[PDB]
Image (cartoon, coloured by chain):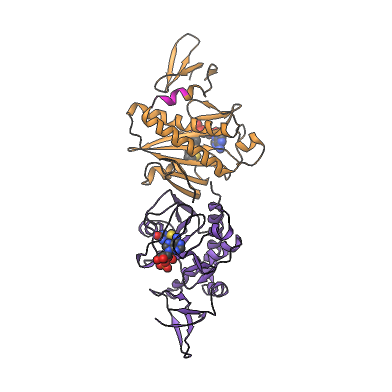
Chain colours: A purple, B orange
Amino acid sequence: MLGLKTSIIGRRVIYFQEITSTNEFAKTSYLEEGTVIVADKQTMGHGALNRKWESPEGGLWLSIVLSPKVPQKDLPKIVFLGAVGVVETLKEFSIDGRIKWPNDVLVNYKKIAGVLVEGKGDKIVLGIGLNVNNKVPNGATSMKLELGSEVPLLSVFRSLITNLDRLYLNFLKNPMDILNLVRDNMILGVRVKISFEGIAEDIDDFGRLIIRLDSGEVKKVIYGDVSLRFL
Amino acid sequence: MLGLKTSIIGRRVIYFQEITSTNEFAKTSYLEEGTVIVADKQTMGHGALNRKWESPEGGLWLSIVLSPKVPQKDLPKIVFLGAVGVVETLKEFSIDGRIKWPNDVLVNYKKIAGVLVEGKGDKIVLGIGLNVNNKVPNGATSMKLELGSEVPLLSVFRSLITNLDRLYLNFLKNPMDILNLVRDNMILGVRVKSFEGIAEDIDDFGRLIIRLDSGEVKKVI
Ligand SMILES: Nc1ncnc2c1ncn2[C@@H]1O[C@H](COP(=O)(O)OC(=O)CCCC[C@@H]2SC[C@@H]3NC(=O)N[C@@H]32)[C@@H](O)[C@H]1O
Ligand SMILES: Nc1ncnc2c1ncn2[C@@H]1O[C@H](COP(=O)(O)OC(=O)CCCC[C@@H]2SC[C@@H]3NC(=O)N[C@@H]32)[C@@H](O)[C@H]1O
């Protein structure tokens, strides 16, 4: 009844009034590629390292099952598909979303969304939590708060799925393209703390964050239990 | 993200851009009570016996998984829950649908929806096909044809699921209530057709009561 016209992402959608975690359900269940798991609320939503992810009603909490047929070396870029997809959707709603490497989306430095990719071989789960009309925790914001008015959750879902499908299809053919989209939508040229501090200069051809320390030393950061903080 | 507020029916919804048949998927897949299987189009949709159900894009094609804690004798009434749910939804959109025993809903005698119930173990699958904005076979009708404008498909889904959840919850407690709702919304007092006779009513088992010209009374199951 939804009438989705996407090629892969959104071929099937499993909606829940409530769930423990869409990422957990997606990882555990036998699901086909492109299936989207979405819930009004999560009782056990999480970020990396089992960090609690607040998932009240009003937000967009979903996961997508992917089976990317690309080199093992390109798989780490899936998180960027989620981040860029969220940014594009925010821009469609006239919200200035910017990427905080490697998985966060901010609006005026406040966290509006987070991306979490979990993979176990031939199966990758792309999880996205985006605050829309829900109340948010410390250091966060939502689409409603930035626009000053409520936004139809289904409209945001449709927009995001359409963007992700396009991004994913192109990723399968040209896995390097997503890096340019990340660069054009990420927060750069400012001081950050990885510990060590320096200027976040850019991301390289592997998606590593390039940081220039005061001494001039250049470090390349691989994401994998490494968050950054803005100064 | 759908924000459904129903108690059982619609707790979970599995949507497909395309599927063979929502009833077939519901029957062969393990699904919790209340799960709704819905698809934009069905390639092998079916009615009863071996009939095909035309399921092009634009219509509402869905199945609901039930596991009703009621006596065996009440199971034949599940089809009525679907038919009445459709009638109630149509009324919300200002369309007057009438039930043609035992599973059809007609508008000015043109078929707008059909219901198909199938049992698999202790799981009951309630299938409903309702023409909304899709092309329909000759003689049939759709919400779009009756209203003269494109009808928001999701709005029809929300309405129907809300009505079905209410009808089902009441059925679990008062399984006889659905019978009066059917009677007040079914086509009776007319001749029907193997034998012919007047469709007088439905009895307490949901059987169609027919009065033949000879005066004989037959009960159709
Ligand atoms: N609703 C919210 N909005 C903004 N920040 C939040 C938030 N809830 C928690 N946080 C903060 O964000 C941190 C988590 O950051 P991380 O970088 O590790 O992790 C993330 O940013 C990833 C979050 C992924 C969420 C989605 S919801 C759909 C799917 N199902 C799941 O169970 N997860 C995914 C927490 O430690 C909090 O400080
Ligand atoms: N779209 C349509 N609208 C009106 N009449 C139709 C139609 N498609 C076919 N018909 C006619 O209706 C007859 C079928 O009537 P019956 O009384 O046997 O059967 C029915 O009326 C039941 C139809 C149940 C359909 C739903 S769709 C969701 C679920 N998944 C399935 O595969 N099935 C269920 C056919 O033989 C046709 O003549």
Kindly indicate the quadrant of the structure image that contains residue B139.
top right
In this picture, residue B167 sits left or right of residue A2: left
Q: Residue at x 51, y 67 (%)?
A: A106
Residue B181 visible in the snapshot: yes
In this picture, residue A231 sits left or right of residue B72: right
Q: Is residue A197 above or below residue A58?
A: below
Q: Is residue A179 above or below residue B172?
A: below
Task: Give how far across and how far down residue A142 sits, in percent.
Answer: 52, 60
Q: Residue furthest top?
A: B214
The kind of secondary structure the magenta stretch mainly shows is helix
Q: Is residue A83 magenta?
A: no
Q: Residue at x 67, y 37 (%)?
A: B148
Task: Give how far across and how far down residue B41 sits, in percent.
Answer: 53, 46
Residue placed most toward the observer, A226 or B11: A226
Residue placed most toward the observer, A20 or B59: A20
Residue A126 visible in the snapshot: no
Q: Which residues are magenta?
A: B175-180
Task: Give how far across and how far down residue A129 sits, in percent.
Answer: 46, 60
Q: Residue at x 48, y 8 (%)?
A: B214
Q: Is residue B89 above or below residue A129?
A: above
**What is the count of numbered marks?**
0
Task: Give how far across and how far down residue A120 sits, in percent.
Answer: 36, 66
Q: Residue furthest bottom?
A: A215
Image quadrant where one finds the C terminus of chain B = top left
In this picture, residue A106 sits left or right of residue A116: right
Q: Residue at x 53, y 61 (%)?
A: A165
Residue placed most toward the observer, A192 or A128: A192
